[PDB]
Length: 101
Length: 101
Image (cartoon, rainbow over the protein chains, first blue to last red):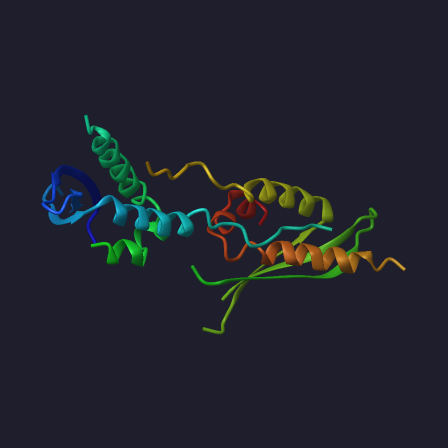
């Protein structure tokens, strides 16, 4: 099953216009099997939306007794988004995260 | 580890005054190892309080992207309280529940 790590880096400009981000999903001992894809911020928005709806899902019972440096911030944002899904079973085993890769 | 079931029954009046309830914790195949104790409604109130504080404990992060028949009702109430703790790891593995028996 390994352990999951994530790194979003290396922003490249596509000939069509939009910038692309390199997404690295590391499966780690100290030897790692890596899975690399390329995504744009729109896909990150979609994933964020799906996860955010998946997230904040709790409580169903009671108790009772009786200078285009914005791509850097986008990079770090997507990175935080991916890293936030590590220690939550609902997000880590989410089908949207698996279809994402 | 077995599977947990609970039955609160057989209300008896203690010579000192207070009524006592028979609490059966069943550890179940179809053959069950039983653990029986006797409790009063005060202990049930204490347990209920500890569990209720233990319960309703969620959310610590963000997301981001940019005719004294009242003893019957008391019996059923305590029974519901015990049965409610089965399918929750935080309540099932609670030390208050283990000290209770």
